[PDB]
Image (cartoon, coloured by chain):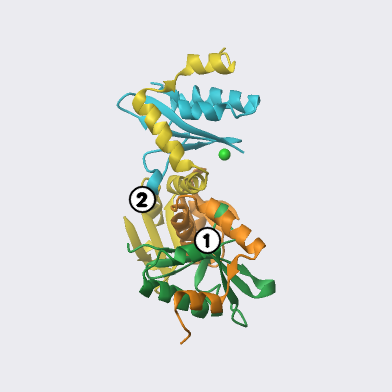
Chain colours: A cyan, B yellow, C orange, D green
């Protein structure tokens, strides 16, 4: 059922810039709700971003791809307010 | 689909037009006196658009995506155990 | 202003809701059973969103706006006489 | 939304560089639009942009667009960017 969630090296660099509470919140979401229902917690993006998805949370957003064939979600970028 | 429709065509079939945009990327421009007056789109579609607007406005967004795409193609990615251990966020 | 309204509230009153959005920046999310199904906005508001997307498709758009804004604050701007002279476009 | 008097239109350095990218017919059309219709009705010819581009306006004629700001107190419009896309 749950997808395998992975962070790119690029997104990992983003994680290092987060305050520790936001860092922990991102990790719990990424390996929790995101892993369970990536099509529900995020939305597919449009125009030149077609093929990527954004999940908006309270203080941060994750940009990701979903590979259904390999039941994987891959995080491209983490942004924080 | 990108339909332009008079309000008279919408009235009485509101359920159906709402159901239609809801499940798709379709848009309806609703005209009044022959002039466009409003647009109807799915709620999910509206969210997709808002998030596209957000992300396109971020610095180095395209370069970010290209670098993250190159990581994906080389297997430069990390899973739960590695991330939890590097950042000190244990499970349980 | 985003309002969230059940579809039962919109039915038979679509003229008034189209009038309410066509003249403003307001949005209406229409629900089925507390679940958002569709979003209604004015035609002008939709065009504002489409033009925002057009500009956001230009790589480096916010950085070029910062540079133009610095131009304005620094007096690096050009008036009609100088522009028509440089580009050889005389009046009339 | 009508303006009583034509606004003074100015191009930033950024917009001027954009003008240089245009072939002469389009370059001349942009100039005549900027100093004519845009000057006379800066609100009516364009749309306000949203979100991170809030505060700017976009006016389109055919395949070109100008991105601009309105300064009412100084009856001035300042063009930030010009873009042309044949489709
Ligand atoms: Cl964010």
Image quarter where ligand 1 lies: top right
Secondary structure, mark 1, is helix
Image quarter where the C terminus of chain B lies is top right
Q: Which mark is residue D14?
A: 1
Q: Is residue B28 above or below residue A38?
A: below
The N terminus of chain B is located in which quarter?
Answer: bottom left
Q: Nearer the viewer, mark 1 or mark 2?
A: 1
Spot occupied by residue B48 in the image (x, y as percentages of width and height): 45, 45
Residue D32 is labelled as none
Q: With B64 as the anchor, is B17 left or right in this view?
A: left
Looking at the picture, how far across and down is residue A8, in whole percent?
Answer: 44, 26
Of all chains, the one bearing label 2 is: B
Query: Relative to the observer, which residue lies in front, A50 or B92?
Result: A50
- Would residue D60 be visible to someone looking at this image? yes
Give the residue at mark 2. Answer: B20
For the view shown, which residue lies furthest in the bottom direction? C92
Quarter of image, res C23: bottom right
In the current view of this chain or complex, which residue is farthest to the right?
A: D73
Residue B11 in sight from this viewpoint: no
Q: Is residue D55 above or below residue D1?
A: above
Is the residue marked 1 within 8 Å of ligand 1, measured from its CB? Answer: no
Does the residue tagged 2 have its C-beta within 8 Å of any atom of ligand 1?
Answer: no
- Give the distance between the C-alpha atoms of the residues marked 1 and 2, in whole angstroms: 44 Å
- Residue at image location 55% in from the left, 56% down from the top: C65
Q: Residue, x 49% and y 22% (percent of image)?
A: A31
Name the chain letter of the residue that bears numbered label 1.
Answer: D
Count neighbours of disc 1 (C-alpha within 10 A) and say few if under 14, some if 14 to 19, many if 20 or more.
many
Question: Is D36 left, or right, of D28 in this rendering?
Answer: right
Q: Is residue C37 left or right of residue C24?
A: left
């Amino acid at each position: 059922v749950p997808y395998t969630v992975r962070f790119t090296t690029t997104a990992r660099r983003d994680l290092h810039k987060l305050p520790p509470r936001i860092l922990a919140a991102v990790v719990e979401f990424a390996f929790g709700d995101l892993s369970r229902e990536p099509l529900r917690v995020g939305k597919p993006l449009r125009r030149e971003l077609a093929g990527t998805f954004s999940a908006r949370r309270g203080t941060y957003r994750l940009l990701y791809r979903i590979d259904d064939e390999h039941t994987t979600v891959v995080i491209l970028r983490v942004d924080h307010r | 689909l990108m339909r332009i429709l008079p309000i008279s065509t919408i009235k009485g079939k509101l359920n159906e037009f709402v159901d239609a945009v809801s499940s798709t990327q379709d848009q309806i421009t609703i005209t009044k006196n022959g002039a466009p007056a409003a647009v109807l789109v799915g709620a999910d579609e509206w969210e997709s658009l808002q998030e596209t607007l957000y992300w396109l406005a971020q610095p180095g967004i395209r370069e970010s995506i290209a670098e993250a795409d190159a990581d994906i193609a080389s297997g430069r990615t990390y899973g739960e155990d590695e991330i939890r251990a590097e950042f000190g966020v244990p499970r349980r």
